[PDB]
Amino acid sequence: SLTPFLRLPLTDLTGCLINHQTYDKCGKFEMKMMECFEAYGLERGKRECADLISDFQECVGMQKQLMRFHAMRNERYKQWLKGERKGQEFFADPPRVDAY
Amino acid sequence: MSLLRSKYYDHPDGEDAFGKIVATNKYAVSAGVAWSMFDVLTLSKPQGYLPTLGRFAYNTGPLMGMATAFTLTTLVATNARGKDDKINYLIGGFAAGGVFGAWKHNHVAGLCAGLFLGIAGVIKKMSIEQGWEFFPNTPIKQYGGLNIAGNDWTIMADPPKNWTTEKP
Amino acid sequence: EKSLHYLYEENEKAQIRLLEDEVRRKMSERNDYQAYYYRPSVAKYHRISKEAADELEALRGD
Amino acid sequence: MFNNSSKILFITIMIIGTLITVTSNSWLGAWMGLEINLLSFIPLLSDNNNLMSTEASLKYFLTQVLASTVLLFSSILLMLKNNMNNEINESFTSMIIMSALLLKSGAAPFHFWFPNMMEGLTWMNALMLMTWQKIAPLMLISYLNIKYLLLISVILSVIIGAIGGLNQTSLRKLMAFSSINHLGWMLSSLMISESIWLIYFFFYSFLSFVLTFMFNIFKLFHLNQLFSWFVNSKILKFTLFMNFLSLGGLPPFLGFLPKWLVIQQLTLCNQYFMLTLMMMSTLITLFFYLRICYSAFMMNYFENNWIMKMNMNSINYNMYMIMTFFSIFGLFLISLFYFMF
Amino acid sequence: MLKIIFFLLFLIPFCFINNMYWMVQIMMFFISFIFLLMNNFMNYWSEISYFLGCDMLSYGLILLSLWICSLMLLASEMINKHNNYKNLFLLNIIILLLLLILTFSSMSLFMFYLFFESSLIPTLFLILGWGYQPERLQAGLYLLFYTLLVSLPMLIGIFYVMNKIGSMNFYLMNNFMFNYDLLYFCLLCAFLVKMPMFLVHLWLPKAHVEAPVSGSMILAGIMLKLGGYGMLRVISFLQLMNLKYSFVWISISLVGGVLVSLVCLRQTDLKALIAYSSVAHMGIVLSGLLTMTYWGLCGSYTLMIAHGLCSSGLFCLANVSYERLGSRSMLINKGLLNFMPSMTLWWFLLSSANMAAPPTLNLLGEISLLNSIVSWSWISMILLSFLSFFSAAYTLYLYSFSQHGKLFSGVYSFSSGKIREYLLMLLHWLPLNLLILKSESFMLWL
Amino acid sequence: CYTDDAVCRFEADQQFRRDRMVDNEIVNILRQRFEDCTLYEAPDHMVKCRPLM
Amino acid sequence: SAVNDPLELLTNKGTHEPSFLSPIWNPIACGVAGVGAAIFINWGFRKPVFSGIQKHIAFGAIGVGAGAYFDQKRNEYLAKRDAVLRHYIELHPDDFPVKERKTYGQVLESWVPVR
Ligand SMILES: CCCCCCCCCCCCCC
């Protein structure tokens, strides 16, 4: 997170505006990152919390998961265009709707 | 990852030619396109599709002439004598001033600009051989005065933290 | 001897100024101390919102 | 402020919105504080008996609304890519945030609204525009560690704000171009030390706040109104015009001190070339300061004959002469200060 | 130097009391008397109290500045009779005297820089307020901008030296030495413009012709000596870069002073010819400084003090004849011996002092500054002989054409010489002939 | 003397200056001895003043 | 001292006696500034300079009180600054080590001769 410059009582309302602590799956990870952002600081936290920043980033931004999914989808269509994948067996078996 | 993504000082001076031409013309392209973008809308509006590109070429192409003439003059002066020094950059600045004089049809501008760009060249050569940097990364960056931790004035109470300095 | 005393005072002031220049350079290089170059970030508001969401779980119902 | 208590209410919501902006730990709270500040500053600067004040308010509105929407756009993009409030490594969306902040602050090359709008104002709203409305965008620039874009803004601001102020003989546009030139010294201090920026801003606002009072009381909207300005003693006009040499950075006045602390902190942080570029800039600023100083330094003028007595407010001229003393003999307080250690 | 500074600080409220102009002059001459009795200074820094102290160099410079400012009040009587803001003029003189004492009593270089830039403001006030021509605005702007354009990067040099050494004290900075070209150019170009080199002189005749005598004397007698005293402080730790880059400044400052001396032969203005005369002799001073010999520094300081005295004395004569003849030139002021015969004695006694006058301190400064230039190289002999020959060619043309020949036959009746003017001319000449008996206080600063 | 010490560089510089002064009137006194040899041996200074030279 | 220890360099032993103007200069300068400000107010309103001495006395008292208070705040600020510098030196002794003092008898610098 950022820092309050010349901080006053007026930042107490602003500080709780957008955060992941309210019933989100990622917020505990965010909380851990905030823990070292309270310990190391905002400037040492950019270097000594590279593991905790990236876990929160690909937990709420879902960058690596969506790149993985788009690599899984593009390879199947690439195999269909190259002729290795038959058009009848192009898609696999669907999941149950009660699953997930 | 191409020949366009090259710098002027990626090689020693006089060793490489085309990368230096591409780099110095790239700064010439950036300066000319920026000045012509703040030119053709703001003062002397061309009011046409073709005179706008004409003003773009007028503000861009002589800067390519400056860059190419300075780099070729520095390359010739480096390949002529064994030693590399400052007056190669001085005569390259005079060649760029002569290009300015050919642009503006005024010899006096060509000389004065040659003297100014030669002074700029010898100062840049002093920078590259003495090791100091024109715009270095800032070593000392004050984010506040003393007691930046001690002037937290907030009315809400702090909940107890989840981190300790104590070793387990 | 007044020149000797003033030279001793100015030489010690120059030495302390050089020492504090190296101390400030090493402090701003690594952001180690809380005083000068520390940009403070607090996890107070995240803990406040998580605590408020924890009290709001008890008040859900009818 | 003047003639209404609702203007005091607008000043109160102005202070509230700016202090909401600068204390925000998120870009969205800073953005809504800028919305509150814009809401507060539209009604001051609007007057239906002035045909150009409404046009100045429209120019301010269009410039701030365009700059606030780009600021929210790149803030949302920063939250989209790097999901915290800041960015670990600098990228282009930080440059878009900095550019949208530079349009609010009035720095070059996004400076063009600022002296073109200052012709439509009074002097008190000019002082609120070029001092307090530069609190919120300049303090938000401090969160961004960008060197090339800030350096380009510094060089362009000190080049243009010195060169551009030579042509105008109107005092409002000249003082706006002076505020553009002093903005470059603030932005040059913004990437070495935030405290040194605060000190340069406080002393620049002090010198602005004492030079506004000489123009607000006597209604000096032009350069030759200074030459026709009547004083009961020419030594008093000689002393009152020393604040322009203070704002030009000439020692031993007070305004040498913030420029000097910026130069000292820049040389400690190993910047020398843009400091030398700002040496040549402030000579031109001192040059168009001296055309005002022609009106008091020659000690005798061919003056208009009909006016015989000068008139001033009580409390405004009482508060003016406290600070004119400290804008001349302010370097005797160099031992009292303890911020710079 | 706290007693002198507090003496002038409580001499400040005499400006606001009316009819006290000559009282301020009397007490400033009393300051000069006390400062004559304060001489005990040697090589190092003595009488140290709250960052203030002096060596023999700074003692002579403060004594010269005090003598020039007291004479300047004696010189400026047209302020008193016309009541042309005499209180503001007195306050400007006393504040500028405080600033010049404070920039000469500086133990660290940054007080020298700070009060050196502070001293530009009352001189600019004197130019813009107490001149007589419409080109006052061209004069003070040239002075202010030619000083400031080169004195602003020297602040960056000062902070570069401070970070490297950590202090600005002149003895602690003597130990170190630097091999940076741009640091040398910053620490030299401000003094190279402030005391006029031939390529950068321009501001000097514009500032001198326009300026009032109380304003031309502080530009001729002192405030070119700031640009010599600055090099006397700075060249101690930049000896290697000075040996790298002296020859261009010695060549420029020796060709100028011949070209400058040929300029004065082809000029008709009386105040402009002394203005270019300040360039030629401090061309010798500038040539002798950048040769780091012991005789060069000693004779340079001697010619600074003595040339300041004789140039201020020569600018005293150019305002006596100006206020009687309405406007000064060679053509109007031709042959003033038949008008003022007793003024002609001081005219020759101070115009001869501008060249080599035999028992004066100008010759003793010149005879030892030629020693360093001759010992530096033998090529410099050709352009020194022409320099001194053309120097006494022009400075004898001043007295020669202004004080001999037929009258103008178009002038009106003016007042004769007074007791004030002869006393003013005496205190510029007899210090030039009386300090040679103890010239070691004006030779040996080391 | 040490590198950072300035209280002892002042004393060493002052005794260096004083020794330079002392040697200056050593050479000056020897020159006056040669000149007094030249005046006192007015027709025969080519023999008596050669060792003093 | 054969070594230049930063702990021994920074620790105030007490051999530096403060000057006569050291506790008194800021209140008298701020009082002179307040008296001059009231004089400047009376001059600009075309009053006599010493007409209203109530303003002179009030401005002088405000100046002396503000000078004493901010001089005390300055003294605690400088004490905390040197405490911060000392604690940072003891926190990282590897980056600020004990250096051996090296005399001129072991150093060959390049002298610069003129000729
Ligand atoms: C006009 C005179 C103002 C000063 C009066 C004396 C003030 C003395 C210093 C303040 C008290 C210090 C106590 C330690």
Image (tube, rainbow, N blue to C red):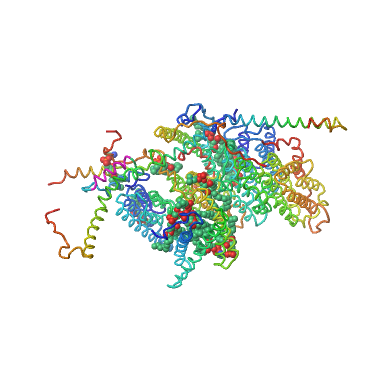
Question: Toward the viewer: D49 or D257?
Answer: D257
Residue A37 on the magenta segment: yes
- Name above or below for residue E161 compared with residue D87: above
Residue E334 x %, y %: 79, 55
Question: Toward the viewer: B165 or B146?
Answer: B165
Q: Can you tell which quarter of the image residue E19 is in?
A: top right
Q: Quadrant of the N terminus of chain E?
A: top right
Instruction: Report the span colored magenta.
Output: A26-39
Q: Can you tell which quarter of the image residue A49 is in?
A: top left
Q: Is residue D88 visible?
A: yes
What secondary structure do most residues of the magenta stretch adopt?
A: helix
Q: Is residue D49 visible?
A: no
Horizontally, residue E27 falls left or right of residue B116, namely right
Residue A59 x %, y %: 25, 50
Residue G59 x %, y %: 49, 38
- Name above or below for residue D333 compared with residue D57: above
Q: Quadrant of the C terminus of chain E?
A: top right
- Picture mark count: 0
- Name above or below for residue E68 compared with residue D79: above
Report the residue that reaches farthest toward the right: F43
Horizontally, residue B157 falls left or right of residue E313, namely left
Residue D245 x %, y %: 55, 49
Residue D234 on the magenta segment: no
Question: Toward the viewer: G49 or E258?
Answer: E258
